[PDB]
Length: 48
Length: 57
Image 1: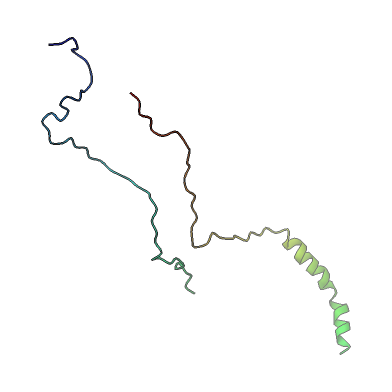
Image 2 (image 1 turned 180 degrees about the vertical axis):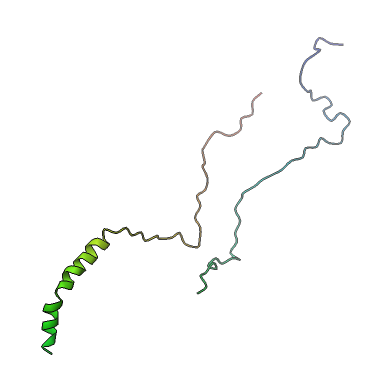
């Protein structure tokens, strides 16, 4: 009952649309650092 | 004990042989391959500075 009809978008009036939540799945890769002194790395030693 | 003088004079040819030893061993290719140690290196990252997120409207 208004001027604005057939506009593409998503207003903030009722975004949930009766849903408890919107979900998304996927894979999540990470290459972050970490301290590992438990190695105490000088074993690759040459057995002789 | 005089025999040392005789041996030196007689064996002097080994001097030229030794000159050949060193002056062609230098010619031959050598490569002492200093390592990286057991502990491995790594740089931070390719990091570039920029202005952060702007709150436009």
